[PDB]
Each structure stands twice: as C-alpha cells, then as structure tokens.
Image 1 (cartoon, rainbow, N blue to C red):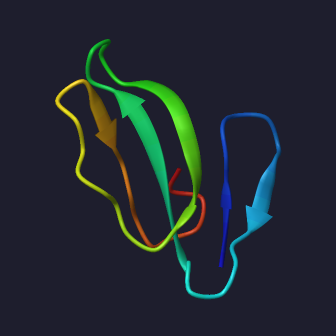
Image 2 (spheres, one colour):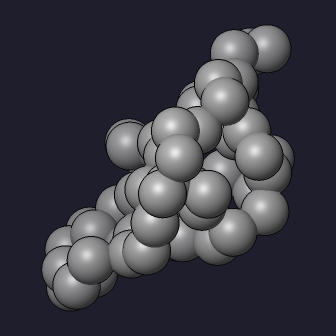
Length: 60
C-alpha cells in the first residue's frame, strides 16, 4: 500500500492504519493539486478545496 504524491517519481509507503491516500485539489481554481498524501479517510471537503481520497495506490 503506497501512493505517489505530486508528479515526478516520488511515492511513499503509507503507515499502518492509513492504508489509504488522497489528493487535495482546489475547487477555487478548477482542480489544482495542492496536497496529496497517506491517510485513512477524507475529511470534510471544503467548497474551495476538493479532497480526492481513495484506497488505491497511485490514485493521487
């Protein structure tokens, strides 16, 4: 269970508990990928920022 952060080859193995990941793109702008990382589950997405969470590696 691992996930890529932004774009060039740089992913990381997620820690126990957090077998999921995400990609916080901004809704303010179209979908600007600001954050990306290893979590468990997505928090409350803000109207200004979309939290694109998943359980599968690479998805972010």
